[PDB]
Image (cartoon, rainbow, N blue to C red):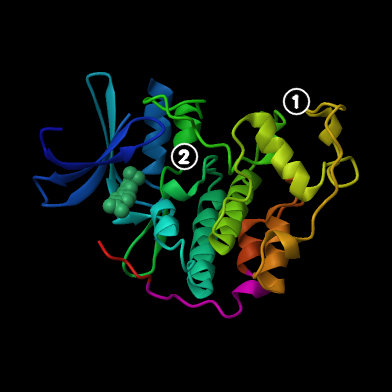
């Protein structure tokens, strides 16, 4: 770590602090994340998982019981970009380009059987060129998803798939498609889709919009560990009310990304072929750094 000069603190992650820093040997500006043998091997497998829409893991440094991850640095995250674009909204062509690139990132990781498990706007990073990249891919399998961060901050439930909330222990790549669907809806409407503040509030917000799931829409739901027959039965809402002014192609794609049954939920690869992307382009965002 004597090879890095900290520039500034860029945030507090789930596992530890994130700094912007300079590598003295190469002159490289990086993001430094300050975090057991099983974690070392898993994190080392991530150094190989390279794609233009995945924040590059440059190095893993393990010294004096501390783990440091050295990543490619990007100048802004999607959460801050969405807040900065609150008054006007992010233009639809830019939302579509970001969704398309995020799906490419997911299709790549999922093809290598690597799940993210904790996608959220905070871990989507953007640059001046119009790229968007997924950060922290693979970290949840290495260290777990805790209730609170190292600073006691509450880990957000807003993008959590219903099978995780219902106690499925062996979840699939579909959990990342659900989280990305929630993010897509939030970019369009400028409001979080399901801003739960407890596990039951998160689940009941999903049920109030998509309908309480049953054996018809989700075979096996009633046998899930945390399912309770006493859950209230709410009716499903039309997407036309949920995500206006999203067009019919976008609403149909979103509906497939939010299917209750993870087996029915669209894959990233199939989502890339959706008619919503017929006119996709790569616009340049308005970024003042
Ligand atoms: N708006 C701003 O000043 C702003 C917001 C976010 C960032 C940011 O998190 N950057 C990062 C993080 C990373 C890898 C995952 C560790 N690479 N790059 C930097 C600057």
Q: Is residue 14 above or below residue 132?
A: above
Task: Provide residue 65's location: percent of width, then percent of height.
Answer: 27, 19
Q: Is residue 25 visible?
A: yes
Q: Which mark is residue 240?
A: none
Q: Residue at x 73, y 62 (%)?
A: 241
Rendered image quadrant of residue 67: top left
Crowding near the residue tagged with mark 1, few <14, some 14–19, many ≥20 C-alpha atoms within 10 Å: some
Q: Is residue 263 visible?
A: no
Q: Which residue is mark 1?
A: 226
**Residue 277 is inside the magenta segment:** yes
Q: Residue at x 65, y 41 (%)?
A: 161
Say which quarter of the image contains residue 286.
bottom left
Helix, strand or loop at disc 2? loop
Q: Which residues are magenta?
A: 273-284
SS state under label 1: loop
Q: Does 61 appear above or below 205?
A: above
Is 48 colored magenta in this rendering? no
Q: Nearer the viewer, residue 80 or 6?
A: 80
């Amino acid at each position: 770590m004597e090879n890095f000069q900290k520039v500034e603190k860029i945030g507090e992650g789930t596992y530890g602090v994130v700094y912007k820093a300079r590598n003295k040997l190469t002159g490289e500006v990086v993001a430094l994340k300050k975090i057991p043998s099983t974690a070392i091997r898993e994190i080392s497998l991530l150094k190989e998982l390279n794609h233009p829409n995945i924040v590059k893991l440059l190095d893993v440094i393990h010294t004096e019981n501390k783990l440091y991850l050295v990543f490619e640095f990007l100048h802004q995250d999607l959460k801050k970009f969405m807040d900065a674009s609150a008054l006007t909204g992010i233009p639809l062509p830019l939302i579509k380009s970001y969704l398309f690139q995020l799906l490419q990132g997911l299709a790549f990781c999922h093809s290598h059987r690597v799940l993210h498990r904790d996608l959220k706007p905070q871990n989507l990073l953007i640059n001046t060129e119009g790229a968007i990249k997924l950060a922290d891919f693979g970290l949840a399998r290495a260290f777990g998803v805790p209730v609170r961060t190292y600073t006691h901050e509450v880990v957000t439930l807003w993008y959590r798939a219903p099978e995780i909330l219902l106690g499925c222990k062996y979840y699939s790549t579909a959990v990342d498609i659900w989280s990305l669907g929630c993010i897509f809806a939030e970019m369009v409407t400028r409001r979080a889709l399901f801003p739960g503040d407890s596990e039951i509030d998160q689940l009941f917000r999903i049920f109030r919009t998509l309908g309480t799931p049953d054996e018809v829409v989700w075979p096996g739901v009633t046998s899930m560990p945390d399912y309770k027959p006493s859950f209230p039965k709410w009716a499903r809402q039309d997407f036309s009310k949920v995500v206006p002014p999203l067009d019919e192609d976008g609403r149909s794609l979103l509906s497939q990304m939010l299917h209750y049954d993870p087996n029915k939920r669209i894959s990233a690869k199939a989502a890339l072929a959706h008619p919503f992307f017929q006119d996709v382009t790569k616009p340049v965002p308005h970024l003042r750094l």
